[PDB]
Amino acid sequence: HPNAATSDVNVTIDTFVAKLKRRQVQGSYAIALETLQLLMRFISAARWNHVNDLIEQIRDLGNSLEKAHPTAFSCGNVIRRILAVLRDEVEEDTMSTTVVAEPLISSMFNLLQKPKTDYRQVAIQGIKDLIDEIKNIDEGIQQIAIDLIHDHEILLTPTPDSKTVLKFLITARERSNRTFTVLVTEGFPNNTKNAHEFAKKLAQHNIETLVVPDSAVFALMSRVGKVIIGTKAVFVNGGTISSNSGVSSVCECAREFRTPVFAVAGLYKLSPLYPFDVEKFVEFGGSQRILPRMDPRKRLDTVNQITDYVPPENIDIYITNVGGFNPSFIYRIAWDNYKQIDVHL
Amino acid sequence: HPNAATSDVNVTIDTFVAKLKRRQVQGSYAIALETLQLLMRFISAARWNHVNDLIEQIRDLGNSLEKAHPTAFSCGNVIRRILAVLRDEVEEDTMSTTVVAEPLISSMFNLLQKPKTDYRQVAIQGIKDLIDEIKNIDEGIQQIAIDLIHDHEILLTPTPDSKTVLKFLITARERSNRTFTVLVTEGFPNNTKNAHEFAKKLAQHNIETLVVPDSAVFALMSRVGKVIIGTKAVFVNGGTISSNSGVSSVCECAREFRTPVFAVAGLYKLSPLYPFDVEKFVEFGGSQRILPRMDPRKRLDTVNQITDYVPPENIDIYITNVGGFNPSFIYRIAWDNYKQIDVHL
């Protein structure tokens, strides 16, 4: 389905498309908020009267949105989240229009046994609940996370870019009973500016700050207590795409030294998609920021990448608003929020 | 050869044999001293005039001494040490009686190219030098060893029995610039009393003492900086026989956590023998110290062993009076002091 029907009534589709492609929109948290407001505008304005035609139209809109921007997983997840909230209430509604439906638990096995209302209002409130969930994640993290780190323990941190992780770290430092030393890898080609702001906010709160070059990670790994990841997107197998530069090597460095790896994330950040190849999912950077002068750049073919991937073999915990989960279990948390059909849009 | 010739002239042979079998003599350092004084009495008293008949007689005496006591490696090594000091001076003497002898270095390859004096005085002085070497090892250790351990690092120690290691630890604590926390595994069935005296002498010098049960080793390994071994005997492949109880598991615990392993030893403690099987070399303890009452001991077949073995896969450094060496090199240090023939006595 094209945007020919939604042009005069809905204009904000194309402005979000413009915000993605030229990267005017920044940070998964913000991308999610916009798509929420998009779906808010879609239900409030449209006229449908039919339900199945409506849902499949939403599926096509989400399909086009993910094709417009591949790194906007938070875009794709939010739509998929509302899709499933819709689908449950429709399946509840069809049971009343026809007239045991309660075997034991909420399982799977969709290959075995076969099969006017206020539905739109529920769809409205379903968006509102998603916003409030994205608004408050930190409260759900701090009750699980600030139980695992001890006094006189040194914390090494790749990806200082995450707003989520920094605020988790500040709530722990607020506790006068807890003392920890912070090592921060720079992440030269991208994270530098963000890493420097990270080091500034730690000094602002008076926490023992240590700025580390990306070479020196090995030269400290014997002294490191724990490793924390500021992830962007979490996957089925467990693995993460993080907010740029110098993570993968640090995780490899941690595993060889058998140093524990922590990850702080949200369920909206969590994705039901599978990373079959890193080659497709990871976004590459601009080599302009590395080396000046273009006549030597004929011979200097420089390689730089923004997003960094970690395989599930390294990290052990994904502390969310719900709780702490192991990478060998995180798939269930995903299927508790997104349906099997709501993947290939 | 029997002790029928050496009975009225030499009496102290049989008193040392009695000291070994009933374990009246204690600690490898003391066993070495006695055998030195035995060989001191053998040269001072005997009449030989011939050299090759003398050396082969000494070989038979050493063969009988090791058969009398298998755990007295320090006995076996000291004889082997003087044997080689003898053999070099004889080979130097035969070159003058006959009349390049200097190819490059001091090699091996005894399978390639073929072949009155003050010799007895040299044999006398050779014993004297061995004593002085055994008298002073600590001076040669402290100059290599107290260079590797840092401030705020936690040291876990199996085998508190060694006089060598404790004195190495006290010289480092003497340095006001160096601070370290000491964890000590108890070693229940044997080391207990010695471990408690170890903890007392650390408090006497005011070093942060921590007494650890043999179960709790794992529960601390994440926090451990380094591991130190108080070995009794070191071998060709690198591996060690240590002064009793709870070492092997600690070393296994260290390797899994990738925590560094240190060993403090002497060259007289070092052996040219190969441990083909632990089954033969390790001495077993007395089960009386575990469990009382003999009527249940019909059904309670309890297992306890004194000496503990460590494979070379774990430890990394053997700091001696000469210096620090890797287990993949220690064989050369051995061959620099003992000859190839002087093994199978």
Image (spheres, coloured by chain):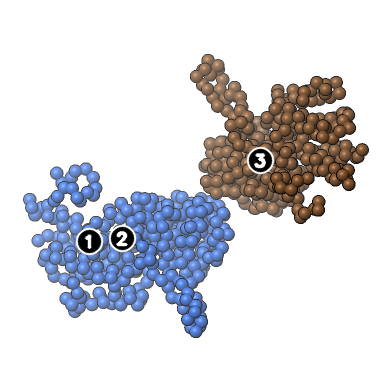
Chain colours: A blue, B brown
Where B223 falls versus A280 (above or below)?
Answer: above
From the image, tell me which residue sits under label 1: A83
Where on the picture, by quarter, is residue A308?
Answer: bottom left
Q: Say which chain tag 1 marks.
A: A
The 10 Å Cα crowd at callout 2, few under 14, some 14 to 19, many 20 or more, is some
Where B57 falls versus B211 (above or below)?
Answer: above
Q: Say which chain tag 3 marks.
A: B
From the image, tell me which residue sits under label 2: A273
From the image, tell me which residue sits under label 3: B235
Q: Nearer the viewer, mark 1 or mark 2?
A: 2
Q: CA distance from mark 3 to mark 1?
A: 70 Å
The 10 Å Cα crowd at callout 1, few under 14, some 14 to 19, many 20 or more, is many
Amino acid of disc 1: Leu
Where A78 falls versus A145 (above or below)?
Answer: below
Q: Quadrant of the C terminus of chain B?
A: top right
Q: Secondary structure at mark 3?
A: loop
Residue B242 pos. (x, y %): 64, 37
